[PDB]
Image: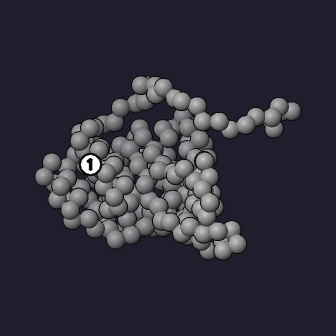
Amino acid sequence: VRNGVASVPRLTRVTPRQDARPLDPEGTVLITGGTGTLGALTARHLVTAHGVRHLVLVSRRGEAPELQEELTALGASVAIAACDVADRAQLEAVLRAIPAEHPLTAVIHTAGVLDDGVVTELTPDRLATVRRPKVDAARLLDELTREADLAAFVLFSSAAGVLGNPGQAGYAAANAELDALARQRNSLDLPA
C-alpha cells in the first residue's frame, strides 16, 4: 500500500532489451564460487560466448584444477586464490592480485550455501551464515568495485526470495536482499 493505493506482486513476461553495455574482451571478470558447478558454468559461458581470456575465481577452497586446465586450454589465463567473498581483507588482497594490465571488467556473484530449515527450527546463526557469503559478499563487491570499469554485476539469487519456498526463510531473506542491493546499484546507474 503506497500513497493510499494497494498493489499485488505478479510475474510478467519480459522481452529483453539489447541496451546493456558490452564487456571488454581483454579484461578480467570476477566470478564468486567459480569452483562450484554454477561458477564453473558461468566461467565457461563467459569464456565461450563473450570471449574473455582473463578470469578470477573466489571460493573457500581456492582451487579448481579441472576448470583451471579447461580455461588454460581455451586460452584464458585464470588466477585463483583461497578467499571467502564475505571476508574483507582476503577479498581486498585477491582483487589487488588482479593485474593492472587487465582491470576487473565485470563482477559475477554465484556464491551460496544452503542451510534450509523450518521457522520453528530457525536460529539467527543460520541467517548470518547464509547471508554472509551471498549478501555481505555482494555488498563487499559493490563497495570495492564502485570505481572499477564494471559492465555486469550478476547476483545469483534464488526463487526462494521471490516466489517463496517452505523451510528456506533465511535463504529467501538472502535472495531478497540480493535483489534489493541490485536495485540500489541500478538506481545509481551502475550495472546490476
Tell me what residue is drawn at x 42 percent, y 40 percent: 152
Most extreme residue toward the front is: 166
Tell me what residue is drawn at x 50 percent, y 66 percent: 114
In this rendering, the answer to whether 11 lies above or below 174 is above
In this rendering, the answer to whether 95 lies above or below 154 is below
Quadrant of the rendering where the N terminus is positioned: top right
Q: Is residue 167 left or right of residue 143?
A: right
Tag count in the figure?
Answer: 1
Residue 91 placement: quadrant: bottom left
Residue 94 is situated, as x and y percent measured from the top left of the image, at 36, 62
Tell me what residue is drawn at x 31 percent, y 51 percent: 41
Residue 85 placement: quadrant: bottom left
Residue 30 visible in rendering:
yes
Most extreme residue toward the left is: 73
Nearest the viewer among 135 and 160 is 160
| Residue under label 1 | 44
Q: Is residue 103 left or right of residue 163?
A: left
Q: Secondary structure at mark 1?
A: helix
- Mark 1 crowdedness (10 Å alpha carbons): few <14, some 14-19, many ≥20: some
Tell me what residue is drawn at x 44 percent, y 59 percent: 111
Q: Amino acid at mark 1?
A: Arg
In this rendering, the answer to whether 132 lies above or below 165 is below
Nearest the viewer among 152 and 88 is 152
Nearest the viewer among 116 and 93 is 116
Residue 5 placement: quadrant: top right
Q: Is residue 117 left or right of residue 144?
A: right
